[PDB]
Length: 306
Length: 306
Image (cartoon, rainbow over all chains, first blue to last red; front, side, top):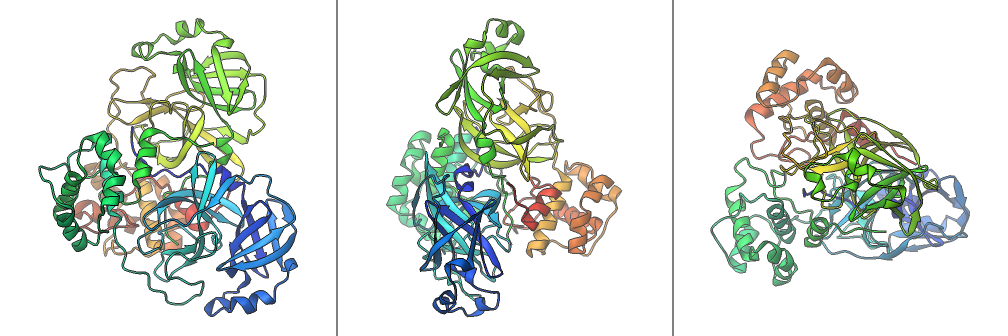
């Protein structure tokens, strides 16, 4: 037993990371088959980033202006195109380590692992959530752009995120692998408002189920509630409204524990109103929202990859 | 910027995991050169585990009684020996994916990544600390025994932990890769007391430095203290006593931030005495002790591996 914030095994993604250099800017790329995917702002200086015209900047670039290095091998660039906010560099070699993969656009509140990289080399792996306001709270220094987020399903890597920007507020913004930003963000160094963020209610409930499975039960109370009553409380505490779809996704955890979803809602309501009184749940002194119902089931049932 | 509990990239270790079966017990092994390393309790049934005589049980086993599977390849066992609490199965093939590696016995309070595995297949990676009482607070289900903990230094994997036991209290015990338990534990299903645990003070101070670097500063106060005065408070709150060795290891973070170590001690003293008043530090509502000073520097300076 026990419950940890576990990332996916990173090896299939490590084999896809490369370094991309254009003029004096270096960041990370993702090499799948004969295409390298990277943030289009690889073509910008710090000064360009204040107000970039990506079309005009890219016209000044030829195939030979992109240096792509896979460990020690230089790749030969034979094509370049811009798709939304990503560059696709066609190269003359297929990556021999390409895994089974898909490109996925995830929903707010879904989780994924980030392989943080610098100069095309991996430094670490961690699990995070796409916030309801389409930011992520990552760990990203200068040079981490082009680092990717992913999920694995047995032998298939679903790439969902490419890192582009740190907002002036210190949270992180990026794209899907088609180059479409999550949320209202642009690849420009300017003031950019993130929405009001909210807590991912269905994830907190999943994590309360994980706690019960692990024996952490002190928070279970004598009350029930309604979906409408609970949602009045969710509004006050800036929690996402719970829907029947969310109730349905929690079904298996309800079944395993014998705790009706609305009973678990009443327990959460009491924690929102009364706080935790200096107590912990699964070693946390706040309500955790970075585990999906699918994450809890995976971890509690020991699902493996290959 | 930002600060996450980051694990090492797991690919070099993924290539070393194999499945070991003896009679009707299956768990994980680690294949390095022509040796597979696994918990000796692979030779026990559930019933044997109550009071095992490992010497007598192992005598009943021959090379052909150990089934070792690397993905789909069966390995041929040509030798077996017991070293403390590990079995070393000599096999007739060197692992082509063996990384540069060492075997290290870590100190209480040091951190490492765990690759959780079932049936020789990786499920996830997470970072944890060896507790001062030589337990770990992991995520380990039935079949996870033989999963390993490690650190990476550029291209070299330092293996420090192999998982053996869940104690009746739900924390986790294991060995170094020479088969010597961390702490007083044995590979027997019996009541086993873990010591009183303590908080890893030098790690909490490292994490307060990480917070300041990231802009989380509200906890900095007007006071200083002495090593002896601080340690009186450390005793009361079950924190490890701080030594000059610990002060010296914090030197670089002191230098970077311009906050003397004893000033940061006085800030910590005030947090121990007054609590956090419903506030957070790096998104935590408790004092975090799973980052070493070396972890903070690594993460804050973007060190990479290969």
